[PDB]
Image: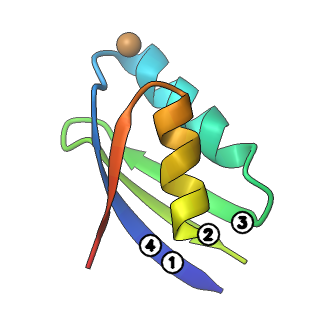
Amino acid sequence: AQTINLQLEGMRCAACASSIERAIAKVPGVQSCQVNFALEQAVVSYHTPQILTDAVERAGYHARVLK
Ligand SMILES: [Cu+]
């Protein structure tokens, strides 16, 4: 697969982590997602990084790919 790391903004509580995890899981192609709450980071494996960041932004959070 391919794996990307995202730096997120706007997570304020566990419900935010859940919303983001759900937004990512509704993206066709995604295989796996983990969120680091304190650091506002996600690691996502998928089968379109722009697809992922766009989904997170639609859920109401900022997202950028880390390189
Ligand atoms: Cu929240």
The label on residue 3 is 1
**Residue 38 image position (x, y, % from top left):** 20, 36
Cα separation between marks 4 and 1: 4 Å
Q: Is residue 19 left or right of residue 12?
A: right
**Is there CB contact under 8 Å for labels 1 and 3?**
no
* Residue at 58% across, 84% down: 2
Check disc 1 and give the amino acid type.
Answer: Thr
Q: Look at mark 2 in the image and give the residue it sits on.
A: 48
**Quadrant that contains the C terminus:** bottom left
Q: Earlier in the sequence, mark 4 or mark 2?
A: 4
**Residue 41 image position (x, y, % from top left):** 30, 50
* Residue at 73% across, 78% down: 47
Q: Look at mark 4 in the image and give the residue it sits on.
A: 4
Element at label 4: strand
Cα separation between marks 3 and 4: 12 Å
Cα separation between marks 3 and 2: 13 Å
Q: Residue furthest bottom?
A: 1
> Which quarter of the picture shows residue 58?
top right
| The quarter of the picture showing ligand 1 | top left
Decide which of 64, 1 is in the foreground and name it. Answer: 64
The label on residue 41 is none
**Is there CB contact under 8 Å for labels 4 and 1?**
yes
